[PDB]
Image (cartoon, rainbow, N blue to C red):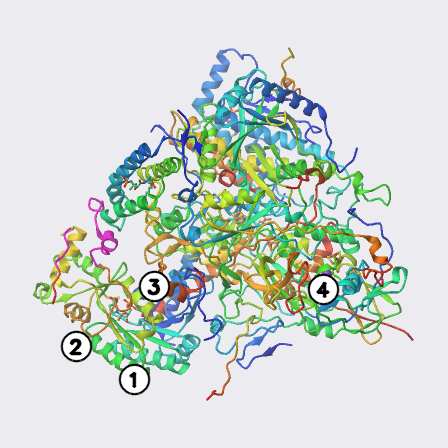
Amino acid sequence: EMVRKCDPHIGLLHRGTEKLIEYKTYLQALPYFDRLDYVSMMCNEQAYSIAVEKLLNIQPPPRAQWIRVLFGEITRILNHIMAVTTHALDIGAMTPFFWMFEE
Amino acid sequence: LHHAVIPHGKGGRSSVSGVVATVFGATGFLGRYVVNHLGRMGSQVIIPYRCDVYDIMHLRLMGDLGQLTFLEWDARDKDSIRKAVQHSNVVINLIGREWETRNFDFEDVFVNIPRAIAQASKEAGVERFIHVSHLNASMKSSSKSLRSKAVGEKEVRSVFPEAIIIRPSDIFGREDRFLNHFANYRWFLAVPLVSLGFKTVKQPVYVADVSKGIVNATKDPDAVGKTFAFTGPNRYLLFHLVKYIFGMTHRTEPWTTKDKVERIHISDVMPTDLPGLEDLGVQPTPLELKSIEVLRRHRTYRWLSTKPAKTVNY
Amino acid sequence: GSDRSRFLEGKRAVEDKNIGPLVKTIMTRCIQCTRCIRFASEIAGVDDLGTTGRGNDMQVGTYIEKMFMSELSGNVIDICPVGALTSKPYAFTARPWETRKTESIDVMDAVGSNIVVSTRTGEVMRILPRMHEDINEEWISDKTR
Amino acid sequence: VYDQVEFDVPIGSRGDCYDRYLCRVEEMRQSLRIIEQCLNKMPPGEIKVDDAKVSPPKRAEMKTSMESLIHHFKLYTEGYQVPPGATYTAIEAPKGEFGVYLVSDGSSRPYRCKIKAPGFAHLAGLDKMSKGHMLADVVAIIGTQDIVFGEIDR
Amino acid sequence: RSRAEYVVTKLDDLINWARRSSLWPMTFGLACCAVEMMHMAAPRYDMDRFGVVFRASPRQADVMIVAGTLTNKMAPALRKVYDQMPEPRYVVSMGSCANGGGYYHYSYSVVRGCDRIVPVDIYVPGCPPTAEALLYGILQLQRKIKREQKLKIWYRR
Amino acid sequence: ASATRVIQKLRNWASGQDLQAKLQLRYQEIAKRTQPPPKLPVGPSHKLSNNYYCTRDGRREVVPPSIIMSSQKAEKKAVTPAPPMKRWELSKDQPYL
Amino acid sequence: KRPTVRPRSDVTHKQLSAFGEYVAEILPKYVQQVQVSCLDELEICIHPDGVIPTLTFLRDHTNAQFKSLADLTAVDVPTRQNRFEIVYNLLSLRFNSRIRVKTYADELTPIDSIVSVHIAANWYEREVWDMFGVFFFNHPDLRRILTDYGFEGHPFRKDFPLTGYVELRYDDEVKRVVAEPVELAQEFRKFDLNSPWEAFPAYRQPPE
Amino acid sequence: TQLITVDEKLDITTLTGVPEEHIKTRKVRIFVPARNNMQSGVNNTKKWKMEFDTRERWENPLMGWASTADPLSNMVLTFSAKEDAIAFAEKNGWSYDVEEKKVPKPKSKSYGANFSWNKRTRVSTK
Amino acid sequence: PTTNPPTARKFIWTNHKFNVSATPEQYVPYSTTRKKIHEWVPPSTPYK
Amino acid sequence: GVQVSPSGEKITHTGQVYDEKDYRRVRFVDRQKEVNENFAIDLIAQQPVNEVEHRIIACDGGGGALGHPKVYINLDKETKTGTCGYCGLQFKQHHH
Amino acid sequence: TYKYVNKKEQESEVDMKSATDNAARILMWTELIRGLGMTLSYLFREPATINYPFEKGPLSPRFRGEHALRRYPSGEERCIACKLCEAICPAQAITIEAEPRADGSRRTTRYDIDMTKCIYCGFCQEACPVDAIVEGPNFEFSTETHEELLYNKEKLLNNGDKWEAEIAANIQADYLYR
Amino acid sequence: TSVKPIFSRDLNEAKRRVRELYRAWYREVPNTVHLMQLDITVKQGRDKVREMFMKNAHVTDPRVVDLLVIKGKMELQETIKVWKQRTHVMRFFHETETPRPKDFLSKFYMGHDP
Ligand SMILES: NC(=O)C1=CN([C@@H]2O[C@H](COP(=O)(O)OP(=O)(O)OC[C@H]3O[C@@H](n4cnc5c(N)ncnc54)[C@H](OP(=O)(O)O)[C@@H]3O)[C@@H](O)[C@H]2O)C=CC1
Ligand code: SF4
Ligand code: SF4
Ligand code: SF4
Ligand code: SF4
Ligand code: SF4
Ligand SMILES: [K+]
Ligand SMILES: [Zn+2]
């Protein structure tokens, strides 16, 4: 019953995202981050936007910043629901999975 | 030639080989390997079918997008045959049964359907027609199916004088009715061999070899109006073949019919005057090399993880 | 330049010309830089193009209905910075970002002008000159183009 | 405006799956608190940066003005040019720290884009966390590590 | 027509009704599209109400929902799992990745569509297509396997 | 919202929470699907004067990084990359769960 | 003041310049360059021989305490002799700072792995080897982590094609998933999205 | 003790992983790209480029798209120097054709030449 | 669309069609461009 | 309008039709080749010429922001109506 | 600031009543009974299941569904073959070929969008300067073959003519935001 | 013309590492064929290994030989613990690919590829 060694083999979802991004433009490479973490879409968008905005030495308007923070926290709620409910589903409980997926 | 039939590319999946082939028996055992080779080099394969779309569904992965055209047809619908062969330069005929139904019999399947297909192909003006008969189906054979295939050969040569006729031997493969048949004799008490199988001599031929020969006959300018004999490199007795298959398995739609056992006990003729796989550019791989992938599914767990049968000249 | 406009008035519009089947003229886009006029005066040597009028109404072209066809007449399509003088065979065909550029040599005459073949999706779409100071400078003949 | 909003940070004390689950739930609650603050303090104003060389203009401005049409054309064909340089921008992702290392060569395409995943390091550390444990235990460790594989593999 | 063909047609109706009323999938789920799959499993759309059972083993599966990006490292696993599934099996590809490669079509390690590996019955377009649209694809699959006439083909053999 | 009082009391007692006050099914309190047309405001650069782009070109103010020391070009107290981080204060709202 | 321009604080620039001088004078044996960007990010470029001492000093120093490795990556610039630029981003939680350490390598000179210093460097250096072919000395288990099994070539290199060299498909004749030389139904259309006019005069290189 | 001698040409073709067809049969071009004469800017004529020889692009039977069979069709590499491109090409084992940087010749531009007393440079219009 | 009907246009379909997949009236793709390279036509009369 | 070839196949508005001996019409065997019935060239030919009173007219295609970018057409040629490059509407100056 | 999720203040001692409470909790399954009770409460709520296909999930006019090519009210195609949609298309799913029409208009001869390559991101409909290409609200267009998702200009124009009564209304509802 | 060695000072112990790697591959080929149920025989698998080695045999740079040995050890270890599957092993033989003959007449008859 012991776990003596654990070796996770990955790359089963390797997509060459960085090579495609460096072969595309910045706006064209923006929706790649939506599919990098397909639960934290606005958060990846926000991180990429902050990186490009830093490199461009520009800042978004305050309303855009407030909207980005609001949907970042909505996305945090989405992702924490995803994590907690899938953890409970793997342990064996699925009614919170259904409830929080209605949410 | 037309501008859309000029070959292009390196012969891959997305290339164009310039082959527009209507394959009639594509839903069978040899037909899947033929369609696999055609779509592998990249060709416009028209599949007329009469069974279910679920039954033909395994053919869909087997070519590029739009390179395979599936269409329903009926053997009594010469209009459907004409609509299948209307836009093609090669028509390949693989229609056959090992038994007789109440709707189609041996004479109909081996004569009337190939004659109608070749007549429609001649009316549509296709450049090449290939018809697959069977070896030692010469004439006046003991079984009805071989005589029917002989009459069908005569009718196909009458209506389409330059038809390439290919006579392979008993074809073995993963989904064949030869090696799986001999493996399924073990489910009974013993092995029912007539004269203990000593009088019958057979040289089985691999299904991939037959399909490569068919494709090279489509692409070969010298194969027009010829009859080929597609046979394996080694001749085995029936008893030695049964010994080899049972020792390779390590153990120790009707299942069988009178025509089937008659064709089993009919010996294979010597191919002397006919050209063959080496003349169409295919090296005949042996059953010893290509037998493990077939008989592995009949083994047990202890035997999941054998001397060849000896070869005669006659 | 700036990233926005303060022009709240109505823009002017100029009727087009028909100087030939090679150069399509949409003269509303013209910014009156006299590059075509100077090229036709100095290199083509025809003295056919010019400015008629005064002020904002000053129009580049020919005053009469005259067909401007000499050799070396696609170079006005080259040197027009705006899309006022475009190529009529190349009209509405491709885009510069999608066209691939292949540096080759012209064989229409024995000058051997260095050219770029602009090919999109495996089809030859355009012919442009290459800068070679010892052969053809910046220009190619009309037959070449 | 995370410096402008106020919230609490859930801190565990035992370092196990239970503490991580409690931290994630209290992060949900603090996220709801920040959502309340954002709803109450949403300001008026424009929606993109007022710079048509980076953000595209409005469609009416694009269909009316020459500069707006030109900038819309260039932004939606070539895109804005980013000045050359390298940055590493890391934000607090829900799954951890999301990092982007951008190297720009001065053109309208990024020269290099390395994506740093928290799940990559977490699943690298899966073997340490699974010492002296069970099958259901390593399943629970995978569940509490918040592992997604698109971000891990890229 | 003959009375026997009417009985054969009614038997086809019964068998097709059983197969479309009891449609147990395993979702070979990879990505974004698998997340949207479990949003279709979610209480709003209720494929369990439709008769479609969530989280079935490949040994008990009828249709494979290819949900996500099929990579070169994953394609042999996809083919092996498809081969382990019993013979009355269908394939619903979902999303642009499983359809034709999608946003990673020109990638070195992405199979350009799962139809290069397994025979796809129905393609569901989107990135991700909504759970509403995936349930549309499932009902289209039920109609398609309602259209099957296997005993009719066997009788006309 | 259509539940009877008996079922509502049973649900409230069985869950321990007031459920009818916070229903997870939206009935009428949500916004209308048809909205009046908006009028979005304009940004700070929407002015007809004193709006030269060189005075607000943040993209062109990026400079190459300053070389502190180079191997080809180039008693004091020890320093840190930043002052040490201030300890976080405990929450005055709810410090413990 | 300007709503479209990112605000600039010079205290971070001064602090990072002071710390760059600090690290440069502490380790003159390995540190080749120190720069602070306009984004207030400190980059220290070192010799490949000093990767272990530099990382150990940054992790274990009292003033540094860069105990968290943000990431480990490589950049392929195939115009210089040592074409792979290995970049270590590190985070100091004690001082709330971030640092970047750069070094160089080519296809035939491996650099020392820092698994003994940071444990995430195991998988990160596995990724760097799999994507670029930069070997790492004294690694516990250096092998592929993202590519296909038996994948030939390192795909994140600049000279590696975007679509690759082989593609997988199911062959029914062999009943397998087989690799073919790659053929595209539609070729990837490259776009020349570069303006012929110079954008940033601050980065104008001198003529050759 | 930790420094050896190697007297070869730095061949890494066995480690690049490229198939031997796309090493031996390919030709590469090293060149400064010509200025697009439809514009006047010269920012695209600063960096050396290596490209590959054009291979076959045929027509898809289904959609008419441009289908290709070689992977090195969109491969363009940027270099700061001709010698750097030479080193990269010889290191990767590709046979190269190099053409030197075509620089524009300096020209004597005089605005007063347009209004000459006796020379032919006097213009007839403006 | 009874109190607020849509704007009437002459090119709008007067008969809605459902999903016609796996029907004779399904959609079949083709290249909408004409022939690009024109082959030389040999003369129909012999030289001798 | 939609016309048919001697092969019986409908000709698209781009002028595309398959040849008699072209094999690529087997994709239309047992199916249909759909051609959009409304031809834009015919529909814009049916439009009457707008008779305006100005030497320079402005067109946005109607609807303001719902149309095309606003352009100006110079109606100086009295032997030819001025055509919008976006919407194809024709304008004529009223000189009476 | 920060807060503790599992730390508890000081000690609550070890009292006989507290020990009896814990023993009763882990001998009579009190938390198990209360979990059963609130799962019973959800048994007695109303399900959140809509009646597909007779009931549809709510959407917005911004919804990015099936692609379509629109027209002017005159009937002329809105598309002017300007190729920005395929220039901005991040998946390179749009292929455009163009030539002057018989009346000299700038129109496309080929406008193909691959649904199997498209990522449904709306970049084409937000880069289109004349509102020609749109992502209309159709999403129930799943096909049984891979070919049927390879759209061409005729299919896109047919979709635009079919969905014009809804696409134009959605653009009217939302165009002031964009 | 002086560089830093990776593992081997010169070609001698590099060839020793090559011999050790070839020895271990020759050991593992029958176990590979038996365990992963390969259609091939033991003889032609060893021939495949040998002609892979002869394909790489033309290089004499010690660093390149060391890196080739390292990559061969990775491939071998990947075969030892079975992650590389039957399809990945059978990718070495190209039995589903029609080969291109190298004669000028055949390359002329196929297409424009040199
Ligand atoms: N199989 C062998 O070992 C050998 C075979 N041959 C010959 O090669 C050919 C192909 O062999 P094989 O694949 O094994 O044969 P099959 O038994 O598999 O049948 C071949 C094809 O014929 C079709 N067919 C059968 N009867 C009819 C009919 N009445 N009308 C229309 N189509 C029909 C079947 O379609 P459906 O699924 O709809 O029934 C099937 O696709 C045959 O002509 C056979 O005689 C020769 C030597 C050896
Ligand atoms: S070159 Fe072009 S822009 Fe310049 S004056 Fe001539 S037409 Fe006008
Ligand atoms: S592309 Fe240039 S020339 Fe053409 S309309 Fe725009 S600004 Fe004028
Ligand atoms: S099709 Fe789109 S949503 Fe689905 S897996 Fe691919 S990237 Fe994700
Ligand atoms: S929505 Fe689809 S077609 Fe449009 S730009 Fe995005 S990926 Fe391309
Ligand atoms: S952006 Fe619009 S008008 Fe331009 S080519 Fe695309 S669909 Fe046509
Ligand atoms: K011009
Ligand atoms: Zn207009």
| Residue beneath disc 4 | C86
- Between disc 1 and disc 3, the foreground one is 1
In this rendering, position of residue D101 left or right of residue L4: right
In this rendering, position of residue K32 left or right of residue B106: right
The part of the chain drawn in magenta is: B286-310
Q: Residue furthest left?
A: B195
User: Disc 1 vs disc 2: Cβ atoms closer than 8 Å?
Assistant: no
| Residue beneath disc 2 | B141
Amino acid type for the residue under numbered disc 2: Ser
Quote the CA–CA distance across marks 4 and 3: 56 Å
For residue B309: magenta? yes
Between residues C114 and B219, which one lies in front from this camera angle?
Answer: C114
Say the numbered circle drawn on residue B32.
3
Quote the CA–CA distance across marks 1 and 4: 65 Å
Q: Chain of mark 2?
A: B
Between residues J90 and E146, which one lies in front from this camera angle?
Answer: J90
The verdict on label 1 being within 8 Å of ligand 1 is no
Q: Secondary structure at mark 2?
A: loop
| Residue beneath disc 1 | B158
Displayed quadrant of residue F12: top right
The verdict on label 4 being within 8 Å of ligand 7 is yes
Q: Position of residue H70 (x, y in %)?
A: 47, 55
Quote the CA–CA distance across marks 3 and 2: 29 Å
Displayed quadrant of residue H119: bottom right
- Between disc 4 and disc 3, the foreground one is 4
Q: Is residue B301 above or below residue B32?
A: above
Crowding at dot 2, Cα within 10 Å, few <14 / some 14-19 / many 20+, comes out as some
Q: Residue furthest bottom?
A: I48
Amino acid type for the residue under numbered disc 3: Arg
User: Disc 4 vs disc 3: Cβ atoms closer than 8 Å?
Assistant: no
- Between disc 1 and disc 4, the foreground one is 4
